[PDB]
Image: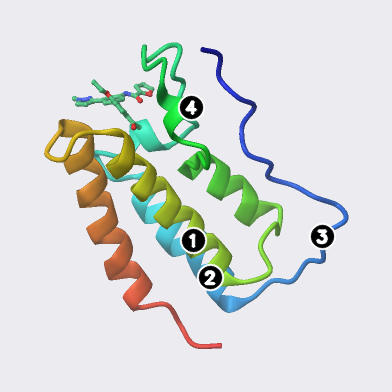
């Protein structure tokens, strides 16, 4: 019924490092996906109450969204680019699990994922 709290985005106990791949994930990948025409349902956690999707968090137990990824990148929450890439993949997979193939939101996520993969293919070395 109710929304869960959003995913955690900061942890002062976790170690921190800035890498060129994490910098690319924020300044290129996140920035580019955020401005896509289809980004807005993915810019914040799914509000299943407001969207009237009462079973959403009965089905989706690893919610993820780009608003959370943006804060995680800003707060140096990730040690590895791969952790951030996994969050993007979780966001897309969540949409494909909850929604019927071919639904409007699924086509929107598919377009975002294609652009994501294009940018991930140009992830710099190190
Ligand atoms: C009907 C089922 O809709 C959904 C089901 C599941 C999911 C997820 C994320 O699994 C998302 C939607 C969804 C949400 C929103 N709008 C926002 O999330 C929003 C709006 C403002 C702030 O946030 C819009 C559209 C939509 C589809 C076509 N158009 C033109 N618009 C679809």
Find the distance from the CA under tag 1 to the CA under tag 3: 18 Å
Q: Do the residues labelled 2 and 1 touch (CB within 8 Å)?
A: yes
- Number of the label disc, if any, that sits on residue 14: 3
Task: Say which label, 2 or 3, has the lower sequence index.
Answer: 3
> In terms of image quarters, where does ligand 1 lie?
top left
Q: Nearer the viewer, mark 2 or mark 4?
A: 4
Q: Residue 109: image x %, image y %?
A: 26, 44
Find the distance from the CA under tag 3 to the CA under tag 4: 27 Å
Q: Name the residue under label 2.
A: 82
Find the distance from the CA under tag 2 to the CA under tag 1: 6 Å
**Which SS class for mark 2?**
helix
Q: Which of marks 1 and 4 is in front?
A: 4
Crowdedness of circle 2 by 10 Å Cα count: few (<14), some, many (20+)? Answer: few
Q: Residue 90: image x %, image y %?
A: 44, 51
Task: Say which label, 2 or 4, has the lower sequence index.
Answer: 4
Residue at the limit of the structure toward the bottom, as seen here:
126
Task: Say which label, 1 or 3, has the lower sequence index.
Answer: 3
For the C terminus, the quadrant is bottom right
Task: Mark 1 and ligand 1: say if the CB distance to the nearest ligand atom is below 8 Å.
Answer: no
Task: Mark 2 and ligand 1: say if the CB distance to the nearest ligand atom is below 8 Å.
Answer: no
- Number of the label disc, if any, that sits on residue 57: 4
What residue is drawn where x is 56% and y is 42%? 68
Q: Residue 84: image x %, image y %?
A: 54, 61
């Amino acid at each position: 019924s109710m929304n869960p709290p959003p995913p955690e985005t900061s942890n002062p106990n976790k170690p921190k490092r800035q890498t060129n791949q994490l910098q690319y994930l924020l300044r290129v990948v996140l920035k580019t996906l955020w401005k896509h025409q289809f980004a807005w349902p993915f810019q914040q956690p799914v509000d299943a109450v407001k969207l009237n999707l009462p079973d959403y968090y009965k089905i989706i137990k690893t919610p993820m969204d780009m608003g959370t990824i943006k804060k995680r990148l800003e707060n140096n929450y990730y040690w590895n680019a791969q952790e951030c890439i996994q969050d993007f993949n979780t966001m897309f997979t969540n949409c494909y699990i909850y929604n019927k193939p071919g639904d409007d939101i699924v086509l929107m996520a598919e377009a975002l994922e294609k652009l994501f993969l294009q940018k991930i293919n140009e992830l710099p070395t190190e």
